[PDB]
Structure formats: C-alpha cells, structure tokens
Amino acid sequence: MERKALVTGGSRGIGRAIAEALVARGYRVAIASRNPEEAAQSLGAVPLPTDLEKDDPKGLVKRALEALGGLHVLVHAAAVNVRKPALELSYEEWRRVLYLHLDVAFLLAQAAAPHMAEAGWGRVLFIGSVTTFTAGGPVPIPAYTTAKTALLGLTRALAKEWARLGIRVNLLCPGYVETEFTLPLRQNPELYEPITARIPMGRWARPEEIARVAAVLCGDEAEYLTGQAVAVDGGFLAY
Amino acid sequence: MERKALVTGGSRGIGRAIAEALVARGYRVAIASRNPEEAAQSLGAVPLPTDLEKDDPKGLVKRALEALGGLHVLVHAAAVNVRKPALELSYEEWRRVLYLHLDVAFLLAQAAAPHMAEAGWGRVLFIGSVTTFTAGGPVPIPAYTTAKTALLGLTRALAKEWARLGIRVNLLCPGYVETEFTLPLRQNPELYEPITARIPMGRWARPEEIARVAAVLCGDEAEYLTGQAVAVDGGFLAY
C-alpha cells in the first residue's frame, strides 16, 4: 500500500470508520486500541493492541513503524471521558481525560513527526468536537471540552512548526455521530431532543460520513490546508 | 455528466481551477464570466457570457438550467475589488465591491436553491478569504474584507435554512494564491515579504491546490458538512 497510517481508537466508532476509509484509499493501516484484532481482520489492517491510557506513546509509534515499514499518517481517535461537572470531578479524573485526549496527542505527534519529515510528506489528524467551540450544552463535560479545545491550539502550533517538513496538521471536529461512545446520550429524550433540534440537517451523522472528510485531511487534498479545524456537524454550530 | 454545476468567475484564477476540478469529477459544468469561451473550450464546459456586476443573477441561473438540464452546484468565484482605504473609498466603490461579492452571492444562491431542492441534492460554495477572519494586513481593502466576512454569515444562514432540502452551503477561504487577481500584490517585496513570512509553508498556493478542496465541498464528501468556513491557507491564519 501507498501511505502508511496509524489510527488510534481505530476499532470502534469514528476511529474504525476512518481506518476503513483510509484502507479504501489504498493506505496500509495499523489500528491501535485495547482489542483491535477483530477490526484489523475485518478491515484488512494491522492490529496493534495497546492501552494508550498507560502505555508509552512513542513505543506505539515505533511498533507502527516496524509493522508498516514507514509512517505518513497519524489519526488520534482514541476515546474516553468522565461526564461529571467541575465541582464533582476529581483531579485524577480531570487528568485522565486530559492525558488521553491531549497529552497523548502531543506525544504521538512528537514521535511520528520525524518519520513523516524523513518521508517528506505527512498528515496528522487530531479529533475535536463541537465542544472545541462550545461547552457541550445540556451535558456536563468540562474536562472533555477543555481537552478538545486545547487540541485546536496544539493543531495550530504543530502545523506552524512542521509546515516546512511536508507535514500538515488539522483538527477534524465531528458533530453528533451515531456511535457506541454517544450511545448513552441518544437514549435520553431530554438530552437528545434539545441537541437534535439544533442540528439543521435534523439527524445525527453516520460514522462513515465523518470518515469521508477525515480521509480528505489525510490525503493530497490537504496539501495547502494546515493548522485548521474542520467541523462536520450537520450545521449544528451554524444554527 | 452527473452533477450540474455553475461556476462564476470560472475563466481565470481560482474559479477556472475549480471549474477544471469539477469537470475532472465528471460534472457537467457551465462557466460564467465576461469572456468564458476560451476557458469553456479548453476545459470542456459550457460558456455563459455575462457581466455579473450588471446582469440579473437569476437570469444567469436560468441560462445555466437551460444549458445543463438541471442545477446541483453553485460556486461564486467572480472577482473584483477597489483597493482603497475607507477614508478615500466612495460609497459607489463600496457598493461595487459589496454588490458583486455579497449581494450577487445571495441572489445567485436564492435562484439556484429551488432547483437543488427539487433534485434533492445541492452544494453552494461561496469563496471567502483570509480577510474573512482578518483585515488583510499591509493591504488597504476594507470593502473586500467586509464582504468576505459577511459571506460567513450568509453561509451559516443559508446552510440553516436549506439543510432539510438536501443542500449544503459552505465558504471556502483560500489563502494567498498565485493568480492574476493577486499579481499586483506579489510583484512588490514590501508587501509580499511580510505576508509570506506569515505563511508557515513558506509559499503561495497554486490554484489547483485550492480547487482540490473546492471539489470536496461540491461533492458527497460534504454530506454532513454545512454552514462552515474551510480555510486553505498554508497555515497563514494559524501562524
């Protein structure tokens, strides 16, 4: 395969859809997650079992390099969250969310960049949220909101630093998507109704619809597109 | 051809590159401009001679419908500007810039929407600028800045209104691109140097690089992407 890609959180939800879209583009893909074997076998990707809440990120990148024979694309779609308001949230919980979403994003990108630079072409795709621009509405998710907003700053910073190395860095911000990660949200009218009423398209996205844009940001289409957030939200933020 | 597209300002610069990219996607394209015949013949599109600074916009849309047998995509890339500071600018000049960039955007979209709605699928692509987010730096372009920023509001408004009609509306914001429209800017060190120093990628874009993203926003990739600005600027805004 052409481009070599590593997708964390690639066995479920959005990550899985992105991995599938990249395989469809002819990329050699490695899927990292706690239990990536089923997804890897089904999608035709390389499985890299890992617990990114504990395992050294650069170690995962090394494994990806060894498994793929190079590294051009990094998509950090790993998911996790502690849905509690700030007054209830413990520092440990705050750190758990910020570590996986933000610190690991930095560590993975830092480790992957030299390989992309050597190849003279790279794409880093961080995953944001509508909470990169708002506070989540009826849902108490301060840590998640902070982390997903922080990613926009990291995106701009790395895009600036690595622009001359052939690397493009962007933040894909999906809106409300039908996935297991959002399963608890959709199964409650008091929350689903008010949120959906603000989506002009009147429906939540299918993971594959989000992946179409992720693929663009991981390809030649993004040659002159870097340091930006791209929201794919059915019109939610515009409402 | 599949999708039917109308591209204004499609015989030169960014518009021409977008028209070419759409033809490459298998779309039946109509190019509108003062003298679109050479471009239409070269690219394999339908020429629609028109002076959008004077001719009724809905009349152009009608001609496009007749020439293409339908209408799914509208790209308003027509260009014009009066580079004078606010204290020097006359109301007539202010209106000239706002009319072509903004009023005509509204009139063209308003006329095209019913046809897209009937087809159950549509894409409206307005063209912004880095001045949709800033004031142009060393260049005195208040009218242009105002118009290109206004387009973001129009984009959100129309995206919201037409979401359930199958229409997606977005604003492609190109950075500094090598075109004849920007020819006077590039031929002056005192202006080119300070601007380029703020582009992380260290170079201006080729029209075709911008068109790659325009094509995405005029295709199925943008199914769940609406009411947004997408900046393709080599990292300029992020710097």
Image (cartoon, coloured by chain):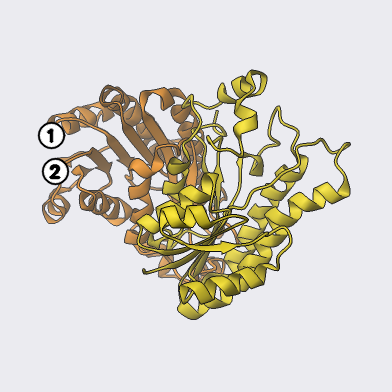
Chain colours: A yellow, B orange
Q: Which numbered circle lies on residue B159?
A: none
Residue B237 horizontal/vertical position (percent): 57, 57
Amino acid type at image mark 2: Val
State which chain disc 1 sits on.
Answer: B
Residue B185 horizontal/vertical position (percent): 43, 63
**Residue tagged 1:** B67
Which quadrant does the N terminus of chain B fall into?
top left
Residue B87 makes an appearance in the image: no
State if disc 1 and disc 2 touch (CB < 8 Å).
Answer: yes
* A190 versus B11 height, above or below: above
Taking the spot 48% from the left edge, 75% from the top edge, the residue there is A70
Q: Out of B119 and A30, give the one closest to the viewer.
A: A30
Q: Kindly indicate the quadrant of the structure image that contains residue B77.
A: top left
Q: Out of B199 and A67, give the one closest to the viewer.
A: A67
Q: Residue furthest left?
A: B41
Residue B47 horizontal/vertical position (percent): 14, 43
Q: Residue furthest bottom?
A: A118
Taking the spot 76% from the left edge, 41% from the top edge, the residue there is A82
* A31 versus B48 height, above or below: below
Residue B238 makes an appearance in the image: yes
Amino acid type at image mark 1: Ala
- Label 2 to label 1: alpha-carbon separation: 7 Å
Residue A67 horizontal/vertical position (percent): 50, 73
Label 1 element class: helix
Q: Out of B49 and A125, give the one closest to the viewer.
A: A125
Taking the spot 63% from the left edge, 66% from the top edge, the residue there is A108
Determine whether, in the image, residue A207 is placed left or right of residue A141: left
Taking the spot 76% from the left edge, 33% from the top edge, the residue there is A140
**Residue tagged 2:** B46
Determine whether, in the image, residue B86 is placed left or right of residue A212: right
